[PDB]
Image 1: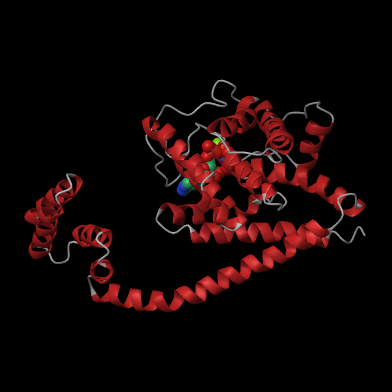
Image 2 (image 1 turned 30 degrees about the vertical axis):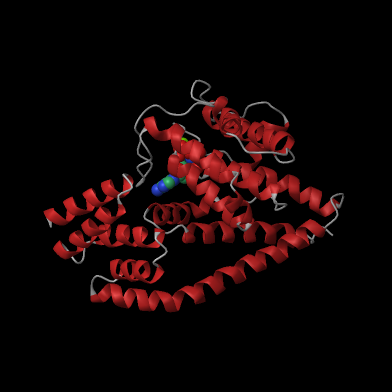
Length: 334
Ligand SMILES: Nc1ncnc2c1ncn2[C@@H]1O[C@H](COP(=O)(O)OP(=O)(O)NP(=O)(O)O)[C@@H](O)[C@H]1O
Ligand SMILES: [Mg+2]
């Protein structure tokens, strides 16, 4: 209905100008011209809730959600599955909480833990670069970082990706983990400057200025990157975010940054480092997304882009448990 679209637009204009009696009559007119106008049902719901008309607001929201019989069934069935899913997901977080407390309880000086923390550190760099096509072996990465002599017939780009990750991880561990106060945009830029500096020092620590494609994802226009990065770091330091479970917080931080895709390259590596900063600041160890999980990783990011972030949170939860199980399993040393 062309009149319904016009009635709604004019209703939102009258609401903005504070004339709510004229807004109400236009909302009613929009629904008279198109009773199934989702946009007008939802907006008239928001308008109703502002006036503390909770029953009317709920009626309009529920109407918007149940236009056709298949929507009706979807809402009935979802209301049944949700509590069962909330309970399954919460159980999994409590299993992770239990294994974190077991790893944390282990005394820092322990011979077994310290050997394993070193071995996994190189494992973690291997996975974070190998997942984007880096063909370096675990032994080659140990050589590059322990000796600081290059490896034969393997591109300097691949080797400088490793050096950058090492530099970025050391920077986080020394400067950011223990530091008190807010996470700034400059903290993210400082991580990116080290992650990408040794491969592309012109672009390292700098937001992109061009339109890009990330697989199936359309990140914001470069003109909007800075605005969304300001809203992002506001959320990072928000009271809401500090009340989230660390794994959820770390997972959402990771997803939100790769969604914005603010750099021309190293967005994944930076997001995974920011993820591990948040976990370490909450007393969890750094976790790995293995090379083998690339397909699953991309699938849950695509699902997040299309309006459900829970599969991504579960995937990060899964990855966290695998890491904790690896630390705990290495009591074989002791
Ligand atoms: N559909 C998607 N939506 C959002 N982010 C995505 C999507 N697909 C992939 N990504 C992320 O974008 C990264 C690739 O962007 P890029 O700037 O090249 O980062 P990178 O650090 O070079 N790559 P990587 O090591 O694989 O994370 C992927 O690794 C994911 O973290
Ligand atoms: Mg890349």
